[PDB]
Amino acid sequence: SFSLLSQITPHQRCSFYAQVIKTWYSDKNFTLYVTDYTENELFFPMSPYTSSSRWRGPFGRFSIRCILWDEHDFYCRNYIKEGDYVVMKNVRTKIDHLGYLECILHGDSAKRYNMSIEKVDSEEPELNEIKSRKRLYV
DNA sequence: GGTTAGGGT
């Protein structure tokens, strides 16, 4: 079953719809920052004051970083783009060294977990709440 | 696995 991002808690498998705000690829992994415009007390508070940054929002604790390893990296890195919507299913969350929630997709997860990330066509009606909530923060 | 909310690869 799906959860709003405000409803996810560390160390539990979860599923959610989100919009991709930022991507970053590296030699090690592929990184997404995603939001559904709901607030979570463990997300990192993104600052509007950063001297140099291409982040335009949302600010505060409204987005979660996802680290994609191995097949998840190879699959998404030249596919998922900023502005896309995604559906992430049965993904795990952890707490990093500084105490912030993060979502991780580890390589070769058991088929039984049915863990996945897929792009959602932007015209899909399940994305309506995201688009509506976005209006509160622009 | 990686380090810390940038960079813009």
Image: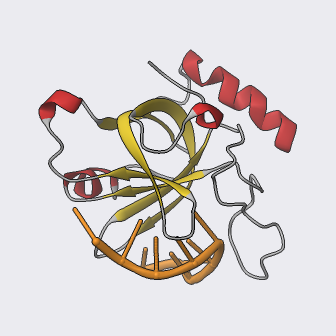
Question: Is A35 above or below relative to A29?
Answer: above
x and y, in percent, of residue A42 in the image: 63, 52
Location of the N terminus of chain A (image quadrant): top left
x and y, in percent, of residue A40 in the image: 67, 44
How are the residues colored?
Answer: secondary structure
Going 79% across and 82% down the picture, which residue do you hit?
A51
x and y, in percent, of residue A60 in the image: 77, 56
Question: Is A125 above or below relative to A108?
Answer: above
Location of the C terminus of chain A (image quadrant): top right
Going 13% across and 33% down the picture, which residue do you hit?
A111
Q: In front here: A96 or B7?
A: A96
* Count of numbered labels shown in the rendering: 0
Q: In front here: A114 or A32?
A: A114
Going 77% across and 77% down the picture, which residue do you hit?
A50
Going 57% across and 59% down the picture, which residue do you hit?
A100
Question: Is A30 above or below relative to A127?
Answer: below
x and y, in percent, of residue B6 in the image: 63, 78
Question: Is A126 above or below relative to A99?
Answer: above
Res A52 quadrant in image:
bottom right
Q: Is residue A114 left or right of residue A127?
A: left
Q: Is residue A42 left or right of residue A133?
A: left
